[PDB]
Structure formats: C-alpha cells, structure tokens
Length: 86
Ligand SMILES: [Cs+]
Ligand SMILES: [Cs+]
Image (cartoon, rainbow, N blue to C red; front, side, top):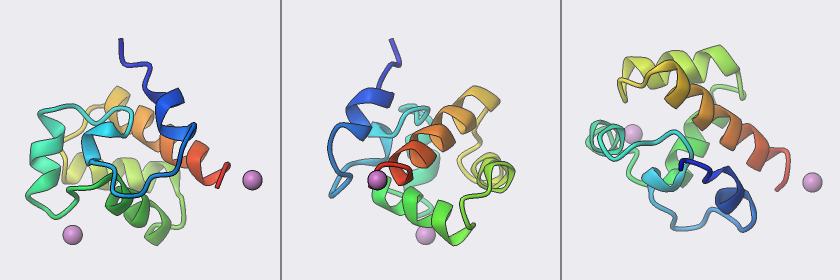
C-alpha cells in the first residue's frame, strides 16, 4: 500500500527524506536526489517557491523527477494537505 498520506501529516517534516512524501517512489527519489531535492523539506520549499500552484509543481516534478500523473498528484496533495495543517 502507498497510504503514506496519513504518516506524513500526523507529525512535522523536519529532516524527513524525500521518499517519505506520498507519491515519491524509490526510483523517483534518485532522479530527485541528484537535483538537490534529497529531503521532503526541499520539495515543500519548491512548492512554496511556486506559490502552491497545482499544475506548476506537477509540471516541474515531471520536468525534473520524471514523475507520472499519480506520483505528481499524490505528492502535491500531501504538500497541500501539510501546508493546510502547519
Ligand atoms: Cs536544488
Ligand atoms: Cs492550521
């Protein structure tokens, strides 16, 4: 199961790795780690630097991590939900 939406939002981000964010696979996490998005805090940062736009974060995550629709959407929802919480 990839039901890690709950585990990410029931505590703060902190020094959490990128692969801990929902939709960030073990393969995606490598393509993301070499660009300097090694932690889930760095992806949160990019999403805020994009003003939390859904299809701009999803456009960048495709243009960089090589993400698919389910991966890019599950990642955005997890960031949006965590922003909506803390
Ligand atoms: Cs970077
Ligand atoms: Cs809140």
